[PDB]
Image (spheres, rainbow, N blue to C red):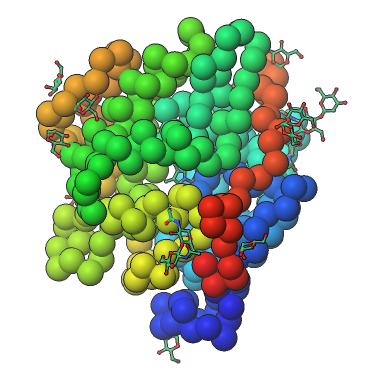
Length: 299
Ligand code: HEM
Ligand SMILES: *[C@@H]1O[C@H](CO)[C@@H](O[C@@H]2O[C@H](CO)[C@@H](O[C@@H]3O[C@H](CO)[C@@H](O)[C@H](O)[C@@H]3O)[C@H](O)[C@H]2NC(C)=O)[C@H](O)[C@H]1NC(C)=O
Ligand SMILES: *[C@@H]1O[C@H](CO)[C@@H](O[C@@H]2O[C@H](CO)[C@@H](O)[C@H](O)[C@H]2NC(C)=O)[C@H](O)[C@H]1NC(C)=O
Ligand SMILES: *[C@H]1O[C@H](CO)[C@@H](O)[C@H](O)[C@@H]1O[C@H]1O[C@H](CO)[C@@H](O)[C@H](O)[C@@H]1O
Ligand SMILES: *[C@@H]1O[C@H](CO)[C@@H](O)[C@H](O)[C@H]1NC(C)=O
Ligand SMILES: *[C@H]1O[C@H](CO)[C@@H](O)[C@H](O)[C@@H]1O
Ligand SMILES: *[C@H]1O[C@H](CO)[C@@H](O)[C@H](O)[C@@H]1O
Ligand SMILES: *[C@H]1O[C@H](CO)[C@@H](O)[C@H](O)[C@@H]1O
Ligand SMILES: *[C@H]1O[C@H](CO)[C@@H](O)[C@H](O)[C@@H]1O
Ligand SMILES: *[C@H]1O[C@H](CO)[C@@H](O)[C@H](O)[C@@H]1O
Ligand SMILES: *[C@H]1O[C@H](CO)[C@@H](O)[C@H](O)[C@@H]1O
Ligand SMILES: *[C@H]1O[C@H](CO)[C@@H](O)[C@H](O)[C@@H]1O
Ligand SMILES: *[C@H]1O[C@H](CO)[C@@H](O)[C@H](O)[C@@H]1O
Ligand SMILES: *[C@H]1O[C@H](CO)[C@@H](O)[C@H](O)[C@@H]1O
Ligand SMILES: *[C@H]1O[C@H](CO)[C@@H](O)[C@H](O)[C@@H]1O
Ligand SMILES: [Mn+2]
């Protein structure tokens, strides 16, 4: 928000306004990075981003401690080297390259289509990067009529998304990514679980309106009473939440789940790519921004 607005106070004492991305700006397949870039906490153009810039942006403006993004930074730069063909040092070339498929970006996302989702031909690919309202609605509908959801509900959401993706993706494309997705499940609990409930740290419940605002608008749900978690969330909270989602009892089993969908997941680890492997082409679509309504500087 505008720095004088005081909207972030006393949690964020140095806010910057929302500015929609323009057609030449680089955006990510990540709703967090996109929100940060829309506020200029990382470059508004989404280019040439250092680790420290990301660390400070997350810590000071989202209540996410450095520990939470350690592996994410490692993988961002692994993917940068893979996509660009050379070491990216400590300047991430852009956000868009993070949508390189079957890498850090993965199938069965909560709010993005898959790279080969619903394509008639094997060489076809689509926008697996920008927010997709229809896709996100398939996640939201699992918790329809609710204001909050818990670990078991999140497990049901990711199963629905796995089922849909496995059915809709071009044959042979779908690849399960439980470890990375469920770190992201933990990220959702970390950012938009309801800290106004007495047992939030032990038993976090996601506020659906907060989640929907963050994902749809790629800005922060301050108007809904959200604020950055304080103290900043740490990695322990995230991986615990991740394990709790995958441990939760499934009471509704979708059909067409991949092998081993139900049950614990492997620890997320550093990515690696063969030098022989050429990257998949990146979707080239202009960056998504909310248009129904468009957002003001304080939104
Ligand atoms: C340097 C830090 C980060 C990097 C490089 C990064 C990168 C990514 C990438 C590549 C994806 C796409 C995966 C996919 O859904 O196919 C993604 C998704 C996601 N990210 Fe980030 N991320 C970072 C930090 C965070 C943080 C701190 C949060 C929240 C606290 C966050 C929230 C999410 C969520 C919820 C998704 C899933 C979106 C969906 O499934 O529709 N990210 N991120
Ligand atoms: C974010 O950065 C990535 C990585 O640099 C950009 O993707 C790459 O964009 C270049 C064009 O600047 C593409 O190069 C072109 O490739 C074709 C086919 O190989 C070739 O015939 C052309 O002469 C040219 O070299 C490159 O393919 C592409 N990389 C991938 C894997 O898709 C991306 O455009 C950047 N996005 C933004 C919004 O800044
Ligand atoms: C995206 O952001 C807009 C702007 O903040 C949301 O629309 C507003 O919602 C706030 C409460 O968060 C209300 O005070 C305003 O009356 C609304 N204004 C307008 C112009 O509609 C919108 O709800 C957000 N989208 C989602 C899905 O959360
Ligand atoms: C991205 O741009 C490429 C050319 O630069 C196209 O070949 C791709 O199909 C893809 O096009 C999509 O996004 C662009 C924005 O660059 C739109 O102009 C197209 O209409 C399309 O949606
Ligand atoms: C914001 O400023 C107030 C008043 O000076 C202060 O009490 C608070 O600690 C500040 N918040 C942060 C996160 O620095
Ligand atoms: C989440 O899981 C990690 C291991 O992946 C632990 O280090 C952390 O304490 C939490 O249980
Ligand atoms: C790890 O931490 C999470 C979040 O604090 C808990 O919900 C979980 O039960 C475990 O203690
Ligand atoms: C990972 O951690 C979660 C949260 O404590 C457990 O519920 C799960 O069984 C696994 O050990
Ligand atoms: C069985 O119960 C779980 C508990 O959350 C739900 O997520 C599911 O929809 C089904 O009703
Ligand atoms: C749906 O079915 C699966 C496998 O049959 C169970 O693991 C799940 O608990 C739910 O009943
Ligand atoms: C229980 O929930 C799962 C996941 O949302 C569905 O696949 C199933 O149809 C039932 O409603
Ligand atoms: C979230 O984190 C837990 C604990 O490391 C994993 O088991 C899960 O697969 C996801 O990566
Ligand atoms: C990480 O691992 C891959 C193999 O999966 C190697 O090709 C790469 O060079 C790095 O060691
Ligand atoms: C990268 O590009 C090579 C050819 O240069 C392909 O063979 C490969 O499948 C990938 O698309
Ligand atoms: C979002 O932006 C548009 C202009 O692009 C306005 O018409 C709207 O009222 C809101 O400010
Ligand atoms: Mn994805």
